[PDB]
Length: 125
Length: 125
Length: 125
Length: 125
Image (cartoon, rainbow over all chains, first blue to last red; front, side):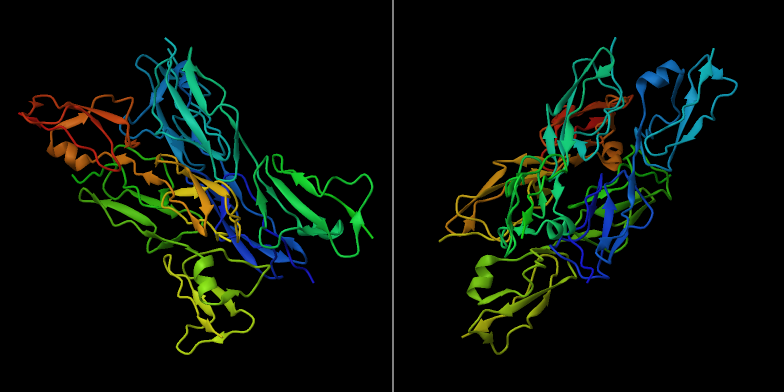
């Protein structure tokens, strides 16, 4: 009893083996997330009692926004080290443009990407 | 006026060029969807008036379900040609298991994958 | 002294971070191989004295050949578990077709994929 | 007569459909190359007389070298538009560093990536 069918696709990830039509109970397969996506949780799913266990999630990278940076009077700190796309968990460092200073209540100039979202610092003249 | 920043990531797809920090108005880039995903719409985005145009969508493949097929008394027709994963737009063909016949109001035995969803035929004894 | 430039592409693999134009000595990045490719060695490269260390290799999966199997009078053992593509290190199990037996000096019916190569068993009438 | 087995893997590319164990004569499948790789030739292979036709090639992107650029006294022209990786067919534009000029017999400052190779311009003091 308890065989499973082919393992479920997940967004932005792939299993590391060729899918089969049927799997014995206790069988397992593993996922990997695509390059700039961070795999959250356990990469392995196991077949038990007719069902696969819960696959991991592939957490989204963050893209910097020209519009937001212009609006907030900030720029990337490191011109030769531009993290245009950042992994979830990775930090991006900004600076105030010439003639501006960190606003009160602003997030720090260094900020961390989480699943697509960057909380940008804000500078004022 | 009207330059754009780095192009947006999309689920299950990738741009075909290396991202740049800034793009001139009229610049374009192109997406491709990952292998079993079907690109819906125009693959190209263009920068105009400070904004990228709308990226395409990557339509999901369909995975056959052992549980559903067992419940509906069906199996794949072609044992040597098993579309365990099907592309959006692609058809999958089932048969009634021995001793069963297509129920009334059942979908045809041939059915088409659309963005992850297969409408399965149902057989009754 | 000793900064590095952008990390080298490798066949069938990708780095897990966004490439930068320059890296400080002691910086590191990591590779992942594409889904059915097996990463051989250490996934991490480190920048020292102006040079990246040696990247890993992505070992090739194996595809079964209809022509070879027909010529050798063999078939896959498990009709519902067809490893049409196998990872390096993974085993594939064949059987002699009806009316044939393992030849003398033949490889065992179970055989392991290594970097694209399967050593097929041979059956004789 | 003339059925084919599963289609061949190619470096840095993937087929766009789920592989099957057997294909009828006249069947076809299609490849796509991974994002910064340029597909050379016809993306489609067709099964005839027991054999697949010849798959396309995925032409390699080019990575700029810090060491070579330093040795040749050049830098990227566009600081905000750095093609750290370039597609085959795509051009990269350099400039002489301050205090240098294009050497005689040097390649032009604009140069095209071909299957991994850039022919770099050289500047002299």
